[PDB]
Image 1 (cartoon, rainbow, N blue to C red):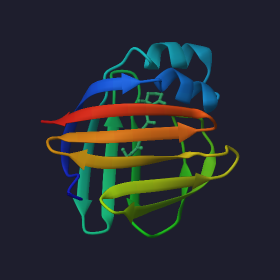
Image 2 (spheres, rainbow, N blue to C red):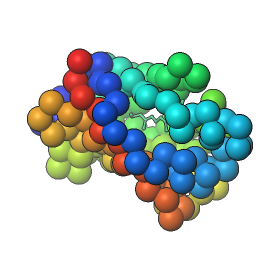
Image 3 (cartoon, rainbow, N blue to C red):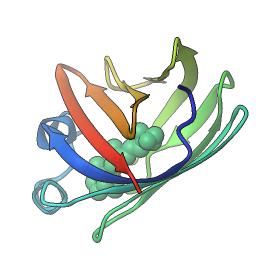
Image 4 (cartoon, rainbow, N blue to C red):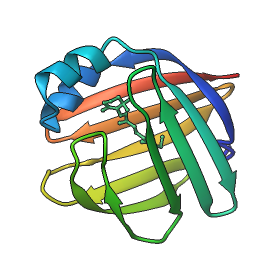
Length: 133
Ligand SMILES: CC1=C(/C=C/C(C)=C/C=C/C(C)=C/CO)C(C)(C)CCC1
């Protein structure tokens, strides 16, 4: 299914530190953020996504329209501009973030009651799993 609406609570987080290191997130921030359980809130209406990813330390919001390239400013992350494009490959939501970093993007998809997220940068892959609230 393509319905990713809802509040999603993290069950699993694999190699988040490697992903952050590839983004050149500073040590203090990495070492706190790797500790944390995340929540994702997604509002999806047709093409239009509004997403909020939260932790006790820092949040990240990004909104986009599927199939419409946009300038993403990764504030609170590595603070870079990328040309972001989110599309559907089957039922997998695929984002490519064009810019300074090679192989940068993510893939997000539903399996049953869970949301899977794969974050890539350079040669690093972070895999996350969230359960629907
Ligand atoms: C790195 C980093 C963080 C960012 C998490 C990420 C990478 C969010 C990705 C959002 C996406 C892919 C939306 C579709 O779900 C948080 C704020 C948790 C803590 C501070 C350091």
